[PDB]
Amino acid sequence: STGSATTTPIDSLDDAYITPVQIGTPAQTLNLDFDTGSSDLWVFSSETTASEVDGQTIYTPSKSTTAKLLSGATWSISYGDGSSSSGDVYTDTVSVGGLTVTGQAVESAKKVSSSFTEDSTIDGLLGLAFSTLNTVSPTQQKTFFDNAKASLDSPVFTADLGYHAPGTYNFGFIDTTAYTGSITYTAVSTKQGFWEWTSTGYAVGSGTFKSTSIDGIADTGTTLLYLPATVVSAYWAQVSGAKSSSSVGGYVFPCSATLPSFTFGVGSARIVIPGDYIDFGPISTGSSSCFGGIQSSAGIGINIFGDVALKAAFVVFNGATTPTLGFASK
Image: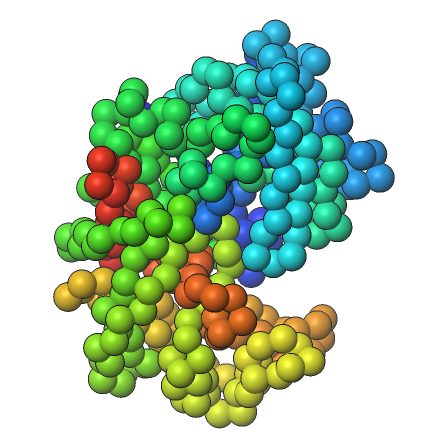
């Protein structure tokens, strides 16, 4: 089997991407944030505290003839941005782009933190990291990809995120029309539960490539590119007027600037992020200070190849017995 679904930016900055997902019988369609940095499929629901729902579409398990309470199971998750959610668990039928899993754990939110409430466009998350990170207790549950894998034509999914435009998540096949050149594959460590790999270096604009190992995660659920402070300083030093602002929380730059590109290494191959992809617009409405898309990871503990990096590439998440990542230009 295979699946193919379009993923759409939630706003004009590509702050995140939503993909329609069918849950239950009859189908209830929710727009979920596919997140290769976490491993829980959770949704706003009929059980979510009413004051914490503000425009999201909810899953109502009592209206699904295939929903079953997973007795005793609870979940609770906190993300790197400080947000969180928690609740109970149902199993139900979940389909993505024509690909169907029966008995998928659907984590129903009883509580969500304010950032989720405040984002009316995201109805929940669909985690695509490794199932070892799933938070369900006392019986940990599998991700949608893990449950579908055996049935897929090939044990892979691909992320093809658009810049200010829709893109595609495919399951079970590699669309050879979606990229240019060849796909370069690179090793993955699953020891932290992430799609963790080692970039071979970077370049700023037309500058010379610096060969240096950068361990990080491929995370579709993080907006920006978080890299070591040395790398980020070298980038922003090429932008007149750019500075790190403690009050704003990162590097800002004059909105009148034209940004240089940023290249990262995948083995001997190179992925070029155009400068425009690094512009996240005014820090506040009407400001002439703009927020940078490349930020320091020094306060995280891990480097994160988020959407800013991934949307410059066609990315293969290879879930074979030994997982690997593939990157191609497009």
